Every structure is written in structure tokens, then in C-alpha cells.
Image (cartoon, helix red, strand yellow):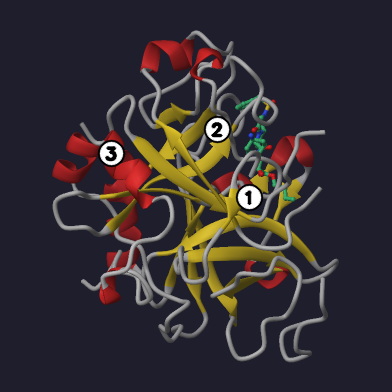
Amino acid sequence: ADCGLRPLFEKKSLEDKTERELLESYIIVEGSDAEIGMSPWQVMLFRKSPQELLCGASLISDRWVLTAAHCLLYPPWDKNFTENDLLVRIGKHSRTRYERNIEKISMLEKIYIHPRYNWRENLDRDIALMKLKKPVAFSDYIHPVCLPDRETAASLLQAGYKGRVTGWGNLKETGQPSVLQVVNLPIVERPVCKDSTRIRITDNMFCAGYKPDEGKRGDACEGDSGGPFVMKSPFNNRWYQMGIVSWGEGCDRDGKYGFYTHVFRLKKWIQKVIDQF
Amino acid sequence: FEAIPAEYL
Ligand SMILES: *[C@@](O)(C(=O)OCCCC)[C@@H](NC(=O)c1ccc2n1C(=O)CN(S(=O)(=O)Cc1ccccc1)C2)[C@H]1CC[C@H](N)CC1
């Protein structure tokens, strides 16, 4: 499609300030302010009443938004949002202001949660799709991210390779940013991920983050859930969403990692919903 | 949060 090519960067042959870090590796707590138009697929899940940031999400077409199922449904915490409870805000930079003439707000038509989403035990298959009431118009600030194909997942989803997470979540586990934050994090070896937690991890998840010894740090935090973990393909220079911010024990704790929904493993379900609805 | 346009709430 035209996915993954940003109007203000790729289209104009301009690079953002940290994309080099990702490409050099190919072979939000402790993040920084995003540049304008740096993540044009970033979406804010916003509750109508009370008005509050619920979660992040991503734009994958003119009508479809991808997020974590737990952002909508999590029985242990009596959470169960329906279409009429939520609004999606697209094209934003500022966390709190209504960005007149820039952002677009949409109502939801339908919410689809993975039928085998495991909220009882380990958040396995933490994924959901949301169909917009009306198609959103693309712009310099609004543009869809690509979904990975088998070949892209295979070559990019490797330990040590860095991906990028963005969101308007808290800056510390223990305030909130004024603008969208960004942080680049390395994918971690599955054994290391398993050995960091008592939670049973599945092939539908992967973890990322720096190991205690690596010196650098960073993580998603409250308000970042549902947001995109993206990587930039060195082959075609497009941005692909490899993961969804799913769960993590605290934020940026030494010895703990962030866990992400594995988008490609659940791609078949994604195609079914869209092809069917 | 800044109030959003009434045509949504
Ligand atoms: C994420 O931002 C979110 O959903 O909250 C947004 C609030 C808007 C202001 C959030 N994710 C979760 O809280 C997620 C949902 C279920 C629980 N978690 C966890 O991350 C951790 N737990 S648990 O009970 O501690 C362990 C567990 C794990 C899996 C299944 C059952 C139990 C589950 C954030 C939290 C901070 C993190 N670094 C990023 C995601």
C-alpha cells in the first residue's frame, strides 16, 4: 500500500532523530519527545465520560484501528468497554489539548476481540480490532502503519534488534508527558523473557527492554498499553508494527521486561475480521 | 484534558 511511509520523513527523504539507532542494530519511561509526524499511525483511545486517556492504539487502514484486548475487556478489574464508551483521537502530538485543525476524532462502529484472548491467566492473544464509524482522511499527521508478512517477521524479530514504542503514558512507575514520547528498545531472547517472570509466556508474545547490565533503560508505562511496537525494514524502508504494548510488571524495573502481543502470529485472525466485516 | 467538540460527547 502506501503504509509505513511517513509524509514528513520517508516521503521527503528526511530521517527522524533516532531511526539510525534501529537500523544500526539490524545486524513511556526514559524516552524523549516525539518529533511532529514521527508516528502518524499513533492513536489515542479516549473515554467519553469521564474524559480520560484509556490506552494507545494504531491506525492500520482508513477504517481500522488495532489495540490490546485488555484495553477494552478485563473482567478482574471490572473493565468492559463498548463502542459507545469510547472515542479514537488520531493525528495527535499534545497529550491533553484539542488540536484544532490537526487531529481527527472518530466514533466506533464495532469492536472485535480475539475469541481466544486469555484474560484469566496470561493475557495470551491480547489483541483487538476496532472499526471506525467513518473513514479517516490521511494527512501529514495521519498515516497507516504496515502489518508484517512472514518474511518481514522472520528477518526483523530477532534478539538484539531494536524496535520503537510510543505513547502518552506516565513517565515513571511511581507524571505524564505534555507531548507524545518515544523510546527505542531491543528485543530479548525468549529464555531471558521466561526466566524474568512467573507468568506463563506463549508464542503469541515477545519481550523487549534493556537487561540490567546494558546501562540504558526504558519501558512502556500506564497509559501506553495497546500502543504500537514498530520496526523499520532496512529492505523497503517502511515501518511495520511488530507488537502491541501488552503487559509488564511495573515500569522500567531492573530485571523485568516489557511484553508485547506478537502481531504476525495473529495476522490470520486480523485478515479474517477485516475480510469478513 | 481540554474539552473536545460537543459533537462527540
Ligand atoms: C497498560 O498501560 C494499561 O492497560 O493501562 C493503561 C491505563 C491508562 C492510563 C498497562 N497494562 C496492564 O496493566 C496489564 C493489563 C493486565 C495487567 N497488566 C500488566 O501489565 C501486569 N499485570 S499483573 O497482574 O501484574 C501480572 C499478569 C500478567 C499477565 C496476566 C495476568 C497477570 C496484568 C501497562 C502496565 C505497565 C507496563 N510496563 C506496560 C503496560
- A97 up-or-down from A229: above or below: below
- The amino acid pointed to by label 2 is Leu
Q: Are marks 3 and 1 on the same chain?
A: yes
Residue A195 position, x and y percent, is: 50, 8
Taking the image as shown, residue A63 lies to the left or right of residue A227, namely left
Mark nearer the viewer, 3 or 1: 3
Whether residue A263 is visible: no
The chain letter for the residue carrying disc 3 is: A
Q: CA distance from mark 2 to mark 1?
A: 11 Å
Residue to which mark 1 is pinned: A71
**Which residue is found at the position 50% from the left and 24% from the top?**
A210
- The amino acid pointed to by label 3 is Glu
For the residue pair A130 and A161, the one nearer the viewer reads as: A161
> What mark, if any, has residue A241 been given in the picture?
none
| Residue density around tag 2, few if under 14, some if 14–19, many if 20 or more, within 10 Å | many
Q: CA distance from mark 3 to mark 1?
A: 33 Å
For the residue pair A65 and B3, the one nearer the viewer reads as: B3
Taking the image as shown, residue A33 lies to the left or right of residue A136, namely right
**Which residue is found at the position 59% from the left and 14% from the top?**
A255
- A31 up-or-down from A258: above or below: below
Distance from mark 1 CB to nearest ligand 1 atom below 8 Å: yes
The chain letter for the residue carrying disc 1 is: A
Q: Quadrant of the C terminus of chain A?
A: bottom left
**Which residue is found at the position 59% from the left and 24% from the top?**
A121
Give the mark nearest the N terminus, 2 or 1.
1
| Residue density around tag 1, few if under 14, some if 14–19, many if 20 or more, within 10 Å | many
Residue to which mark 2 is pinned: A123
- The amino acid pointed to by label 1 is Cys
Taking the image as shown, residue A233 lies to the left or right of residue A270, namely left
Residue to which mark 3 is pinned: A24
Whether residue A110 is visible: yes
